[PDB]
Amino acid sequence: SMSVKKPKRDDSKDLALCSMILTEMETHEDAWPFLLPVNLKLVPGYKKVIKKPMDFSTIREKLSSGQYPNLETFALDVRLVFDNCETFNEDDSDIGRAGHNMRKYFEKKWTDTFK
Image (tube, rainbow, N blue to C red; front, top):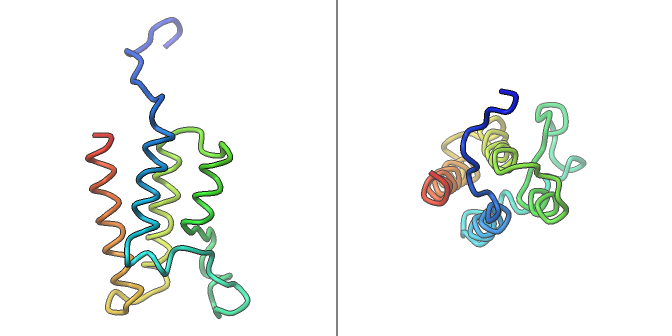
């Protein structure tokens, strides 16, 4: 509360460490469905159904330009990528399996880096 603060957690390396995690996600072999925004002209149903599209390139640009105020808003956009993928893709599809694999991969790096 006012003039009563928990001890200051060091957040000075968060930007660098989120960039490293994002590099690792970008270079995973199963990243291909997620590297670029879904083409809303060429993929029927996507625009209407997925209210907030997100992809790794868009996260990378937001990261590079100070549009994440803290590491939790970064994790929210990464998770949005996989939540979108589950919304639109069957579990038993290549893209559906990719998304599960990537989410697992991300969540381990997140835990090991920050928790």
